[PDB]
Image (cartoon, protein in one colour):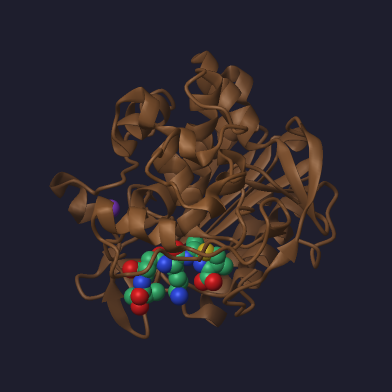
Length: 355
Ligand SMILES: C=C1CS[C@H]([C@@H](C=O)NC(=O)[C@H](CCCCN)NC(=O)CC[C@@H](NC(=O)[C@H](C)NC(C)=O)C(=O)O)N=C1C(=O)O
Ligand SMILES: [K+]
């Protein structure tokens, strides 16, 4: 890389790895549209496998950006509308609380207090219908935001219903394959297992456990090369040749709701750039309910934005940020779940120094 990039990334990430005891890390910076890669540590401590540009990391909540874009692509295809009632796509959802809950609400965590996780004792398609039928909202729809894998995960499952495809098949054919994300996976194939990093949680090697709507909310594993390509695609959607996908990326960066200085997209979250770095979590907050103000109608993707998403599984911590008006971006993938503020701090320190 150019020495300026080299030096800001290594002076920022080296002490981050130290302080947070991160076993393994990959970083990509996208600087004038062009990726630059950096790796440290181990992907598997016991087997002494290093992190490389081909290491797969669990993206956790960053997976939601893929679900938001796949949903955007389905809207652009005319298969769904965000204004549609949920019940249009799941008619057996007959319980009265669902009257007035739209796909917009599900995609943006505004349905009225759907939980962070679907309960572990929900396995089957009948178990999932009972869970949603029996769920009692705390709030009226479109009033309060509570980040929820049960919310955006249901959005993703319903958004693909009119295509006739499974969620994975729609994701593969409509998002991963057009963007040449050939080492990005909902289910890691046997051939790629040698590249799949272990996560580490209290010294113990761990992968993300199966659960209900886990592909749709937190199930994507990717490399630092494919995640750099995902940032480039989201920075510059008009270079994408597949029309509905280009439009789906644009819809995922539209501003649907405002809480404080943040704006809720489909998966992506946004602030106005330039951004105060204390204004940009899990500083160990298990549940953070916030009032939202509708942006009526949604603002199309603002190029002067800090667009980002954090992500965690038990063993992994991910972070993606980018600034369309500067052609700048960053992906940080780690095999430890370390505090969200340390992620945002390091990302800001890097990108600020490069504009
Ligand atoms: C801020 C949010 C919004 S929703 C967001 C969301 C996206 O990243 N989180 C998840 O999907 C969470 C991650 C929780 C991190 C450690 N507690 N759940 C999962 O990924 C799946 C369940 C998870 N199950 C577990 O029992 C734990 C966390 N794993 C281990 C190894 O102990 C697993 O890894 O298999 N999590 C939070 C939160 O409060 O932790
Ligand atoms: K599943």
